[PDB]
Figure (cartoon, chains in turn purple, cyan):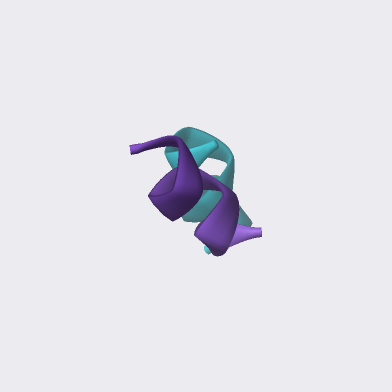
Amino acid sequence: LAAALCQAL
Amino acid sequence: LAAALCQAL
């Protein structure tokens, strides 16, 4: 789930 | 600890 944020940014 | 993730998202 943490990777979701990386994608967004 | 779970809350760290909640904040991240």
